Image (cartoon, rainbow over all chains, first blue to last red; front, side):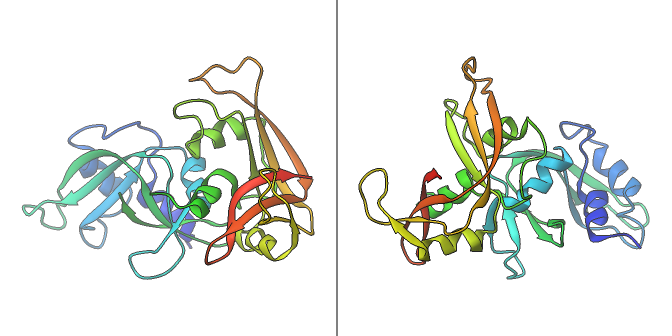
Length: 124
Length: 124
């Protein structure tokens, strides 16, 4: 059964490219990472930094999570990210996305021993 | 505007592990915590204990601070730390550091409500 840590890696990590990649990126990546399986996931962010650098955020700036939980952490440095946002034309099972590149601080929720990212909360 | 307590956590707290895995820890950490932006910060210590354990130092042994203030506190126990010191040949912007692990008492200045560390004074 997929661990929460592994699910975060599948849904949110893409170290293999420095940036957006292409206008196609979100269409390809939302499908290949199985985020269009049961429904079109309406929004999803991929982080283009090393796994060790994203795991290290769990030791950085503690901030409130959107859901009111206390276990969220904001990166001190900006990170290369890609935001995927479902289009209006997008109809399951043909999920369509706008690909946007940004350099922003990430906010992730961390849990466990070891203490690792398990949810992507926000970028700022 | 960053609070002194927040600046202490950014510059000095790395609760992640109980040491530092590689000789490259300080090069990476001095980067990730924004301590190489304008210039290489020459010397900096990271503490690998829980935030709660470090905050509890503010209730431990009262000692004078280097600057002659009276609000410094020495940890009763030794703590896992990493000393980062810039090499003799280090030239901004390629800030280069020797990483050294140690188990030492820490001395911190405490202030505010809550009464928490706001400055790292020394390890002994």
